[PDB]
Image (spheres, coloured by chain):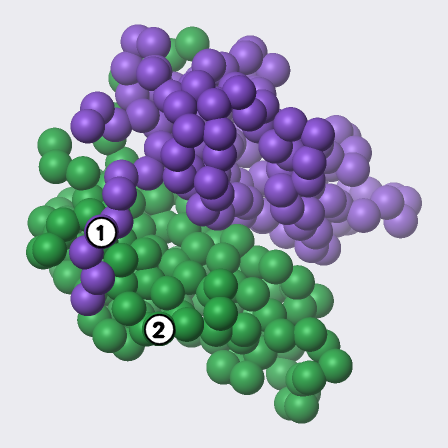
Chain colours: A green, B purple
Amino acid sequence: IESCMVKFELSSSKWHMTSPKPHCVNTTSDGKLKILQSGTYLIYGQVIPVDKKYIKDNAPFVVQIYKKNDVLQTLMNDFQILPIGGVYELHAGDNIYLKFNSKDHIQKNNTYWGIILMPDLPFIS
Amino acid sequence: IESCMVKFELSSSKWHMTSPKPHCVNTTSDGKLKILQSGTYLIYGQVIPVDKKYIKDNAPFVVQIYKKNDVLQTLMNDFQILPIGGVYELHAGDNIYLKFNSKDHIQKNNTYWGIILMPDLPFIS
């Protein structure tokens, strides 16, 4: 029943949390997390790219969400605002993290991500 | 306190909800929302496009989320699965809804969207 949500701010590398020690997730200062409670989660976030005029490298703008050692979601566009995630069934022990093609692509200010343990949605209408 | 989360499934045009009559929003059968409680919301979803190979013109795949008459975000990609949304401060009275560049671009099955009234995140680590 306990509400459980965390939000990692890339600007500060700090997690903002529902409680001092969220029951559903362990978080680390590298922006990674580990699911502690099996259940239905929203994985969410926005990856903000730098203006293309600043990009030095030849790499395309790609964001991957990993679950354990496998890719959960792959996202790409022409260096535009990039909401991430969706509703997933996760299990205790599942590590979740993001991988970027190039860290130089990412505007740290206002880039964030996280999860929320979702309540059941029993009522249809 | 009581969680408040709703999820619209485009396949069925049904909302799935945390409670019989959520306190934080009203919903419409067309997949629109009206915010009843001012607060911080997570807007989320995935918009599934029809395969590129079946779109025989140059019309782009674009999704916009609106708050009343204001564009909250504009998203586009090359006809790939499209996560939407993010954290937004909303106010009582705000209407939230999606608009598509072409309704014909949208696959109903597995397309969904919704909102969550977020818990406060006072603790930082």
Horizontally, residue A108 falls left or right of residue B21, namely right
Report the residue at 33% width, 63% height from top. Answer: A8
**SS of the residue under disc 2:** loop
Judging by the rendered image, the residue that carries numbered circle 2 is A12
Judging by the rendered image, the residue that carries numbered circle 1 is B122
Please state which of residues B89 and B44 is positioned toward the viewer in this rendering.
Answer: B89
The chain containing the residue under callout 2 comes to A
| Residue A2 numbered mark, or none | none
Please state which of residues B31 and B90 is positioned toward the viewer in this rendering.
Answer: B90
Report the residue at 62% width, 74% height from top. Answer: A50
Q: In which quarter of the image is the C terminus of chain A?
A: top left
Q: Where is residue B119? Give x, y as percent.
A: 27, 39
Relative to A48, does residue A118 appear above or below in the rendering?
above
Q: How far is disc 1 from disc 2 in space, using C-alphas? A: 15 Å
Q: Where is residue A71? Give x, y as percent.
A: 40, 64
Q: Where is residue A28? Give x, y as percent.
A: 21, 71
Report the residue at 30% width, 9% height from top. Answer: B20
Q: Where is residue A99? Give x, y as percent.
A: 42, 73
Report the residue at 9% width, 56% height from top. Answer: A21
Same chain under badges 1 and 2? The reply is: no
